[PDB]
Amino acid sequence: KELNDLEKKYNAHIGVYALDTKSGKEVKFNSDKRFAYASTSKAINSAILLEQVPYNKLNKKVHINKDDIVAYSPILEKYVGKDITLKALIEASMTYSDNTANNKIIKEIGGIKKVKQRLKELGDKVTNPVRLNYYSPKSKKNTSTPAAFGKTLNKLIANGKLSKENKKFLLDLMLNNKSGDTLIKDGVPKDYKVADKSGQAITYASRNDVAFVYPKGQSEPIVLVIFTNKDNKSDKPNDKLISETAKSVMKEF
Image 1 (cartoon, one colour):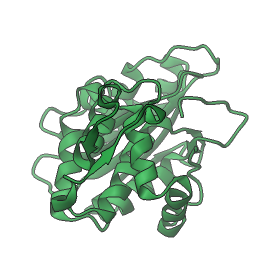
Image 2 (cartoon, rainbow, N blue to C red):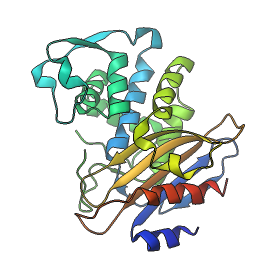
Image 3 (cartoon, rainbow, N blue to C red):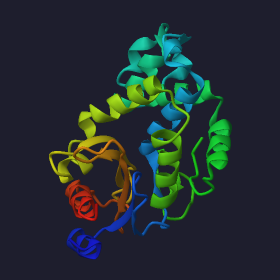
Image 4 (cartoon, rainbow, N blue to C red):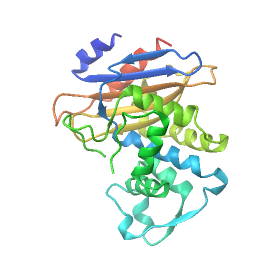
């Protein structure tokens, strides 16, 4: 389906960027347009942490106090006054999208400043991290573009400096996450393997998914970045748009 028809059918804005990492072929649509990136930021931060911690060191522990807790911390809220491992922090953040867990990761890395440093190093001068679920077309805070984010994903993970173990760990989590079942995973041919990280912001029907798509017998992923929003602040997102976009796109591959 034309991408235009999908914007028409859902009365929404779509931003797409796909890269078949084997051939280098690219599919783009509103690729330099800015959208909230928000919670999809989790995969980036965990990824950064994996660059500095060998797999064999994920069992190191950090203390959790009351001052650590942030809203929507399904897992971490139970750790008050205890020690948790780096590995469990990656897990709570990627599988349960735990807020405290993401915040601990960032600190561990050395703060937002250091993440900002790593981004520039990779060639990303677009993505603007926040020191998350908020979006306003006014600002460039918490935004990236499909092309930019797509370039970062590839450089960070698909072809980054991760170990096989670290890469595997992280990919396993994005593979097994039930919170993306309605997105890119709903859209692609059943033979495909999809490791994704969803996102959303509470304003403008800001709904995204990012993935590493592995076609039938192909070892190299297609990086797919889909960013959607709407015209009203209180608009509600429809997950089918993403499903529908993914399906459309996979066809060019």
